[PDB]
Length: 194
Image (cartoon, rainbow, N blue to C red):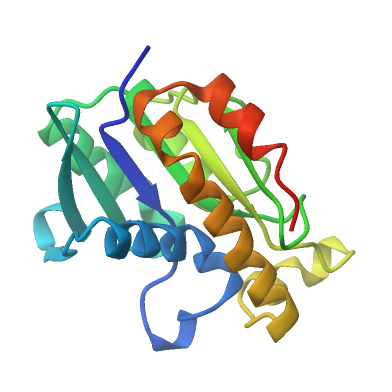
């Protein structure tokens, strides 16, 4: 029932982080911007890269924060407060240790389950966990202690391909996601296979 007004793709800025797994979110937004013909603008006001396109009579904004991951919430609150977008019109794309490459999933609400990007978003938005998430499988290294090194690495090529496939699947439910039909987007998405 609620149109999406903001899609955020999480990542770390900089060449040292480019192409790393923890930037899956931002890869998705970046593909989405390219497919939509949207330009993404270095906007210091929103501590990120911002673009917009028009969908069903409303501006949808795309955000890639350029704070570090752990401070993403600053970027998302600045944009969303400037524009008065409530959490429920926000979709955040992020890497997901709990699914393998090749798998994208959607979720509404819930915790951050250890993602410091989302945690920050959660704290910054006056503590609201009610935004939506596009979870992009990046696999898990199989030990809590290897997590930090893992999300910060570049996946081998098979895993990168399969992340890219999950991104193409995700983009196939763009119409359902922009409209806010999470159930249908879930039905279609969660029925694809990489």
